[PDB]
Length: 180
Length: 180
Ligand SMILES: CCCCCCCCCCCCCCCC(=O)OC[C@H](COP(=O)([O-])OCC[N+](C)(C)C)OC(=O)CCCCCCCCCCCCCCC
Ligand SMILES: CCCCCCCCCCCCCCCC(=O)OC[C@H](COP(=O)([O-])OCC[N+](C)(C)C)OC(=O)CCCCCCCCCCCCCCC
Ligand SMILES: *[C@@H]1O[C@H](CO)[C@@H](O)[C@H](O)[C@H]1NC(C)=O
Ligand SMILES: *[C@@H]1O[C@H](CO)[C@@H](O)[C@H](O)[C@H]1NC(C)=O
Ligand SMILES: [Ca+2]
Ligand SMILES: [Ca+2]
Image (cartoon, rainbow over all chains, first blue to last red; front, side, top):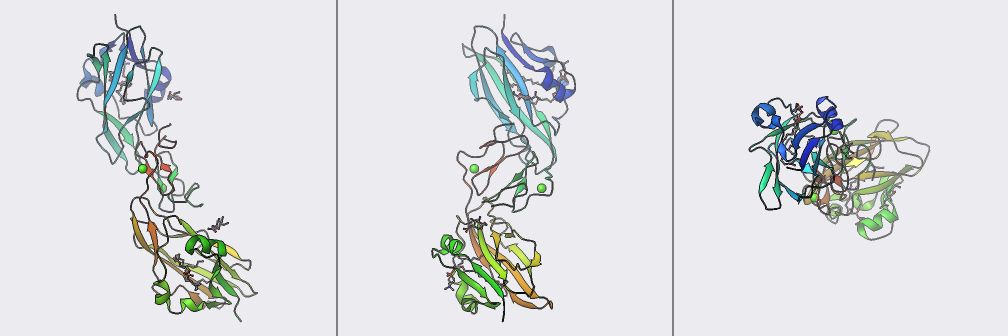
């Protein structure tokens, strides 16, 4: 009956876990079997690696019925390791009829090495306002962060970010914050 | 007898104090009269303004004799306000025969509003190794710093620098740290 789909594309799944196959999360508005026993499923998930700064999810409401998504919580539980996870979409919106990519960003601050715990609480509502899908209650996700080490180091009180670029202050630019 | 000159060019003097005249500091290897009573002179100097991120000094050893300069201390006494002052020259070098510009940088961190105290201790030595000129002993300089306020603010745990640019982390770019 249902028309809702949520999945990780074959390409994104390959960079993440090594297998170039679509990972189905929701098919025809029903959670995939692996997500039924969430705690068993989660214990097979390693922390997101340092080389992964963001993850692409694909979703669609493939029918004539309208669906509404809402990001209730985008929260880092280790703010000194990683800032709040981000989404490249409005927090409340319609699930698109055309399959579209939602990028979840994992902003490691670059000040500390470590594993940051975080939440991505999202609900899907039908046109009656009822919640029909949602992140499993109390779900925790993990991201591995590394301390930034820029080539040569950032001068003029500049800090190195996790993309190996110098974060330069007042009238200071260049690869190591030298120019004016 | 002396050949050493140090001064602030007319243009730099205009943006700094409002008067488009060269400010002579050292002429023919002799400190300018105003620098004799350093404490009286210093009390007429306001903290460097927020709109000034760096200052240009011009120097030359206009004769055949060689002179050597050495920056002994480039230190901020308020590290949380401003990082250590910088120079765009090697710390030990020869004073050029051709008049050349030395840029002293004042790197306000953008985290705090306030006045930062700092030191610029430099000596000039002749070819016998004797110090013939130097910053007056225990000299303190001041720079006004402002807390950075980027238009819209820096997302993804990014910080705003004092040149109103977003300092973006891991796989995050753009005007407010949004893109990947
Ligand atoms: C748009 C983003 C939404 C969704 C936002 C919530 C999650 C976003 C958080 C980002 C962090 C998640 C990454 C987890 C870390 C990781 O390494 O993932 C491991 C697995 C690798 O996949 P795997 O080892 O194969 O697991 C599946 C195996 N099968 C079943 C295919 C045989 O990858 C996975 O197993 C997939 C993990 C996704 C499971 C989360 C389920 C929550 C879904 C909420 C559904 C309700 C609302 C949406 C409905 C349209
Ligand atoms: C290359 C950088 C070196 C030099 C590095 C040391 C200093 C660098 C520190 C940066 C901060 C200094 C800025 C001071 C803040 C300020 O607002 O400056 C105010 C004055 C404005 O100028 P003014 O009000 O006219 O003062 C002179 C008035 N007259 C005499 C012309 C009538 O501007 C001035 O009065 C000029 C201030 C410079 C006085 C410092 C004297 C120390 C000189 C050391 C000499 C020894 C070694 C070099 C010899 C070649
Ligand atoms: C994620 O999706 C964006 C959107 O086009 C794409 O540019 C990027 O290459 C994708 N990344 C992966 C690992 O598939
Ligand atoms: C300082 O000197 C540099 C070197 O060319 C010049 O580009 C800059 O415009 C000068 N600034 C002032 C205020 O004179
Ligand atoms: Ca660094
Ligand atoms: Ca800001």
